[PDB]
Length: 386
Ligand SMILES: Nc1nc2c(ncn2[C@@H]2O[C@H](COP(=O)(O)OP(=O)(O)O)[C@@H](O)[C@H]2O)c(=O)[nH]1
Ligand SMILES: [Mg+2]
Image 1 (cartoon, protein in one colour):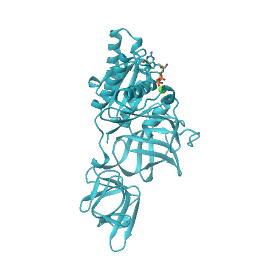
Image 2 (tube, protein in one colour):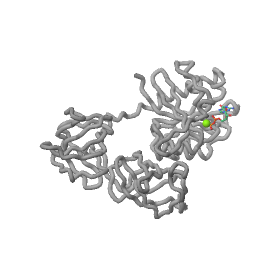
Image 3 (tube, protein in one colour):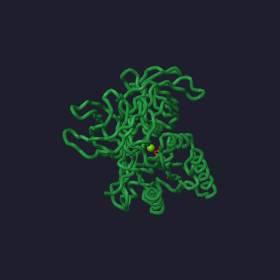
Image 4 (cartoon, protein in one colour):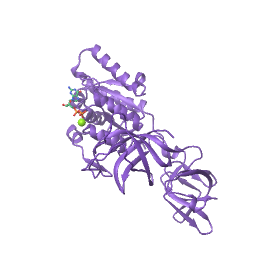
């Protein structure tokens, strides 16, 4: 099967993301095979529901000779904010569209900054509307502006592929400009490395339940998030309390006794030496020395709007909600950015959080913000602090 890669268009409004998305599907369909999509179908994005969050998202698919791509395009900036923090698939790379007529605009900066925060790993640039620009001096100056902006947020601007093109003329059928769509698709193939598959990451299992099995000791159940756990291998129980070491003495799937549990499977793991009461809501099983527990972190959060089922009134710096990490709520206190004293429903802000219990975490881990039982926001860990 062809490798699967998740991409999407980002960049400022009216710079040509949707026209480019249509052009890519159209050009690749007539060149390497597939199904073309038209501008109107993609611009008219369905409402996708992620929890209570409403995100207008168009999903499109296209193939290169060697890869299958799932591409995400959204109508408005508000959708890109929501999608980057809580969208169905995390982008493996992004196509930043920049209109040569306008140059980098405020959401060009914001989407790069968000990409950095939510951990978007590769960004390719399509410099659009070049059918309007005859001057090569201008095009060079815009290209340098985009490279500086990428580097400002630690992307490798100097080595970043930038394709000078015209999404519109390519969608209209002009073969000269279509070649630029193939150049861009070439860069998707060559510049975005194939992402790391979960089965190859160090073992991780969020604990959902614990039982004292008769004559066999303590078992913890959960979905293997990544890696492989084998009978005989050592594990760490990470989070809430001081970290404990243990050994796997059995892997059970329903009534079937296994020798290993793999990423994606729902299993029960028998642990030597651990008593049922030594296990707490919110802990994970992990390969030893691969994930650490933290109480403090920086995050990018989106606060739900009233219509989405969230808060009706803003909160202030004393806000003390619950942060739901994998399996449980942990209370935290927050610090706001300087100048911000109030956070309105529907806002998104950088939030420094201090939980009252440690949670095993790494950059890019998603969480929900909750009040009482109900969800009021969504975040991504941008930087762990300790
Ligand atoms: N002249 C020219 N116009 C373009 C090009 N790409 C897009 N446009 C026009 O710019 C407008 C906005 O494009 P659109 O894809 O909807 O922008 P989006 O908000 O980023 O999705 C539309 O009128 C497009 O047809 C291009 O390469 N050349
Ligand atoms: Mg659009």
